[PDB]
């Protein structure tokens, strides 16, 4: 195995939401085989961000997911050469984002080149007014569509005042190496949380736990 039980994470995100430019660096560690990761994020340019930090967090690697023996693990078999993903996020009030990550490995470290582009967020909506509290736990449906591994998430952000703000994500995943075999259809359960933050979310500690399963308990 190329992948160790303890791996470092290095990340740079460049992006624009509703015209606002920003650059965010990340440093972290995780346990690929237990499906757990945490990372420290720091806004380097464009802070304080004028939109809900929460919209970025699913962009800050399905290598961090506990896969049982009976599901093909496309992500761990992609290394050391690595893989990319592209994601479209569609929010219920017309906000739309496109994100991508190119993931590489050098020694004990995953490097992440992340881009995040958002537009059409209404000025009076929860993203631009900073009314989000968290992502609900979610299930990602994994299947093959025209020869490409595809994940669908139907999820929601909890808002201030007991309301939910619905999001649908579609992610396409592509190994750099031709001839990594596609998996069968399956599920990955996700829980993402902000563990700590400073006043304007210039510094954030982020955690994710993910488990692959075939639907049964």
Image: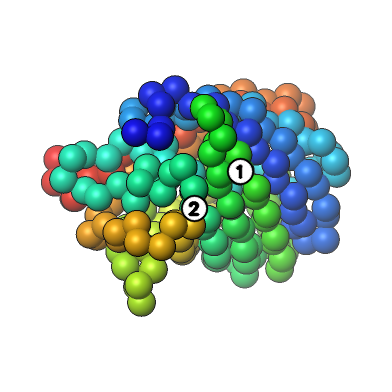
Measuring from the top left, give residue 184's x and y in whole percent: 22, 59
Q: Residue furthest bottom?
A: 146
Measuring from the top left, give residue 76's x and y in whole percent: 37, 42
Q: Please identify the quarter of the rendering in which residue 97 is found.
A: bottom right
State which tag comes first along the sequence, 2 or 1. Answer: 2
Residue 139 seen by the camera: no
Left or right of 19, for residue 162: left
Residue 112 image label:
1
Residue 20 seen by the camera: yes
Give the spatial CA distance, label 2 vs label 1.
Answer: 10 Å
Measuring from the top left, give residue 126's x and y in whole percent: 66, 52
Seen in the picture, residue 156 relative to 26 is either above or below; the reply is below
Seen in the picture, residue 6 relative to 114 is either above or below; the reply is above
Of the pair 122 and 137, the residue shown nearer to us: 137
Residue at 38% in and 24% down: 5
Left or right of 169, for residue 102: right
For disc 1, the neighbor class at 10 Å (few under 14, some 14 to 19, many from 20) is many
Residue at 48% in and 57% down: 176
Measuring from the top left, give residue 27's x and y in whole percent: 64, 28
Please, which colouring scheme is shown? rainbow
For mark 1, give the secondary structure.
Answer: strand
- Count up the numbered dots: 2
For mark 2, give the secondary structure.
Answer: strand
Residue 156 image label:
none
Left or right of 202, for residue 83: left
Left or right of 135, for residue 214: left
Callouts 2 and 1 close, C-beta under 8 Å: no
Residue at 85% in and 41% down: 45
Q: Which residue corresponds to mark 2?
A: 83
């Amino acid at each position: 195995s190329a992948i160790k039980p303890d791996m470092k994470i290095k990340l740079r995100m460049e992006g624009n939401v509703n015209g606002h430019h920003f650059v965010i660096d990340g440093d972290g560690t995780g346990k690929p085989f237990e499906g757990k990761q945490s990372m420290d994020l720091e806004v380097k340019e464009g802070g304080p961000l004028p939109f809900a930090f929460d919209i970025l967090t699913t962009a800050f690697n399905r290598v961090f997911a506990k896969y049982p023996d009976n599901i093909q693990d496309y992500f761990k078999q992609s290394f050391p050469k690595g893989y990319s993903w592209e994601r479209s996020l569609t929010f219920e009030d017309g906000g739309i984002c496109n994100a991508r990550n190119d993931i590489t490995m050098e020694g004990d470290t995953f490097y992440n080149k992340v881009r995040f582009y958002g537009t059409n967020f209404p000025a009076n909506g929860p993203v631009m007014q900073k009314k989000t509290l968290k992502w609900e736990p979610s299930t990602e449906k994994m299947y093959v569509r025209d020869g490409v591994l595809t994940g669908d998430v139907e999820t929601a952000l909890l808002l201030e005042g007991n309301a939910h703000y619905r999001c649908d994500f579609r992610t396409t995943y592509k190994a750099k190496e031709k001839g990594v075999k596609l998996p069968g259809a399956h599920f990955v359960d996700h829980c993402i949380e902000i563990l700590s933050h400073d006043k304007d979310y210039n510094k954030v500690k982020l955690y994710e736990h993910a488990v692959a399963h075939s639907g049964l308990p």
